[PDB]
Image: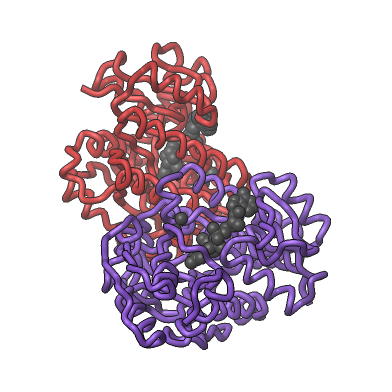
Chain colours: A purple, B red
């Protein structure tokens, strides 16, 4: 049974993943860290086993790893697409340097290490329909460039030092806890909020732009399941995984089915569009399904039902 | 005509490139720099416009650029395959951080920037026969991993900021001016020295491991030609270029044809072999030929003739 360290643990994936790990292996077997502390309304507030760690401080990062003695690490901090184009130096620092430090610690302390990649690692030469695990990688964002380096450097640590590096290329991840903002796939949560508030939604992604997506509970299952797999079953270090693909118009139809009313949406291109257009429409995740049993239990309508129930509970929006 | 800065200029490529640029454009229009000073017998010793610059010193790098106002830059420092496997922190520092600084300067000060890539950017999934410009990139060395990042990051600067970033994936480069080191393709240069000294060459690459190679004068022609090209003629930022491929067995025969005598070579596998085996056997350089006129004058026997005449003259080895 593992002892799990999570870094950048207070963000979108880390919050839900931290809780799930605590449930499965026990709070004493999990250490949750982030450069920031949790808000008083954050789900990890007041919990034991939550610490403050700037992963750019390699000495502090090592200090924490020595003290806790993890056998597994999920290294989550990154600056993602939209922010990274505006603040590329910060993206290069965080996405390259924290990763280098993590991998050096995984070597030194014999840690099985997960670092997520992303469909943003692909660009317009990838083959946009059912994109393969091995293909041409020509990302159009600095974030994506940094994640190609993440994939290749992690794989080198495996080959050279036997570090047990594992990764998936995550699609857009949807969850109810997330505050709608300007992220590349934030149109989807904005749309759920608008529907609940019965207000006009102005969507920055074009209506028929399809992307690979996944609902959070499926994401968490896979993130645990890949780390549990015996090494001998893994034929590669980096796997595509997907939930289902959808466009904004499809998400709108889903919401209208689950609310039984019309939501008003106007499509006005924002910064997310050019980024999303350079990404695949759908992924081939057959290697993940075959090697370690990646599976998906939600479809778009199940997800919409759950979201429309969870958002009022979490954020105080009007319910259906 | 241009004002050309060379960084990392005292090495194998830089020594001959610096002299060619001075000849072509005039000594007052070329500034060359390196972390170390030239020794008294270095071809660049005693020359004006040769300076000491550590490209990890970003303030120093900036100061030099702001003073000289280059219109072109050739950014040459890197830690290469064999050394990088043994000193990976140095390789990651030099290969990533100096590049990051050079690209930012190119953006800020409007410089046309060349940063060489390499066949080492490819690995065992590339398609090893007549490898294309766009393929799967899975390098097996940290150096190669850093060069993929170099290509993608330079290409992103071109896309995001309009930086005129140009690159070729260099094959193994053979030249006489520089004494050979412990690097992968430098077996070839050692084999010429051993032949002239009439002593045993112990070769760490297996006798039929074919690699893309090029003789320096053709390399110099192409390094200048790609930088002279009008931007509108370039359909891509990174080009494969090759001279010809050969194995150590082939080179030995070529040397023996020229020297009219046996030379003694023993093949004792070293680290270079597994690295070379993961590289292409030959490249497709059609895009370079088409777009900007890459061309090649030398074949293996013309190269061997010239190497065997030049080495005695430049280094005092036993003639003919
Ligand atoms: N959410 C998605 O749709 C998605 C999709 C694909 C891949 N990913 C990847 O998943 C990982 C997590 O994404 P997320 O959506 O949770 O991001 P997020 O922005 O919600 O969370 C990131 C967390 O990293 C922390 N952090 C930043 N700098 C740090 C540092 N110096 N030291 C320690 N922590 C630091 C931030 O405080 C934040 O809590 C990232 O690698 C991301 O690229 C996410
Ligand atoms: N030589 C080849 O066969 C070959 C093949 C493919 C690609 N390349 C590329 O060509 C470039 C030059 O290679 P080379 O063979 O001339 O290498 P080299 O090792 O002969 O020369 C490297 C030069 O860089 C300098 N240097 C190192 N750290 C520095 C720093 N911090 N600041 C400034 N200078 C620094 C060194 O002092 C040295 O003079 C590299 O990018 C290499 O990857 C060379
Ligand atoms: Cl984003
Ligand atoms: Cl080498
Ligand atoms: Na962002
Ligand atoms: Na080397």
Which of B31/A165 is in front?
A165
Residue at x-position 58% and y-position 47%? A97
Image coordinates of residue A104 in percent, x first then y, are 67, 53
Image coordinates of residue A20 in percent, x first then y, are 68, 75
Residue at x-position 69% and y-position 72%? A19
Instruction: Residue B319: tell me if it is visible.
Output: no
Residue at x-position 50% and y-position 19%? B52
Image side of residue A108 versus residue A211, left or right: right
Image side of residue B120 versus residue A219, left or right: left
Vertical placement of residue A139 versus A261, above or below: above
Residue at x-position 36% and y-position 69%? A199
Which of B288/A119 is in front?
A119
Instruction: Residue A298: tell me if it is visible.
Output: yes
Vertical placement of residue B164 versus B254, above or below: above
Which of B108/B307 is in front?
B108
Image coordinates of residue B140 in percent, x first then y, are 52, 59
Which of B73/A78 is in front?
A78
Vertical placement of residue A32 versus B41, above or below: below
Image side of residue B97 versus residue B23, left or right: right
Please identify the quadrant where the N terminus of chain B is shown: top left
Image coordinates of residue A116 in percent, x first then y, are 55, 65
């Amino acid at each position: 049974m593992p002892r799990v360290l999570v870094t950048g643990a207070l963000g979108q994936i880390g919050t839900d993943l931290s809780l799930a790990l605590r449930d499965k292996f026990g709070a004493d077997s999990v250490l949750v860290s982030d450069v920031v502390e949790p808000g008083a309304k954050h789900p990890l507030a007041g919990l034991k086993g939550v610490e403050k760690l700037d992963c750019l401080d390699s000495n502090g990062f090592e200090k924490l790893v020595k003290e806790f003695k993890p056998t597994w690490m999920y290294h989550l901090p990154a600056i993602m697409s939209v922010r990274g184009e505006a603040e590329p130096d910060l993206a290069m620092d965080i996405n390259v340097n924290t990763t280098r430090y993590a991998l050096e610690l995984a070597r030194k302390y014999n840690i099985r290490i997960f670092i997520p990649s992303t469909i943003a690692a692909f660009g317009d030469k990838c083959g946009k329909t059912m994109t393969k695990d091995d293909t041409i990688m020509n990302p159009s964002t600095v974030y994506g460039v940094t994640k190609v380096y993440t994939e290749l450097l992690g794989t080198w640590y495996r080959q050279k030092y036997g570090v047990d590096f594992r990764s998936v290329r995550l699609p857009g991840i949807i969850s109810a806890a997330t505050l709608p903002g300007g992220g590349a796939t934030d149109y989807a949560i904005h749309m759920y909020h608008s529907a609940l508030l019965q207000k006009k939604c102005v969507c920055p992604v074009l209506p028929y732009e399809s992307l690979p997506m996944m609902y959070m509970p499926d994401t968490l299952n896979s993130l645990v399941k890949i780390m549990e797999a015996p090494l001998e079953k893994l034929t590669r270090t980096v796997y595509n995984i997907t939930g289902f693909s959808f466009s904004p118009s499809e998400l709108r139809f889903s919401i209208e089915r689950c609310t039984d009313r019309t939501i008003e949406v106007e499509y006005v291109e924002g910064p997310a569009q050019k980024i999303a257009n350079s990404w695949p429409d759908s992924l081939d995740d057959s290697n993940a399904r075959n090697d370690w049993g990646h599976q998906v239990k939600y479809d778009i309508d199940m997800m919409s039902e759950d979201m429309l129930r969870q958002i009022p509970i979490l954020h105080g929006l009007p319910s259906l």
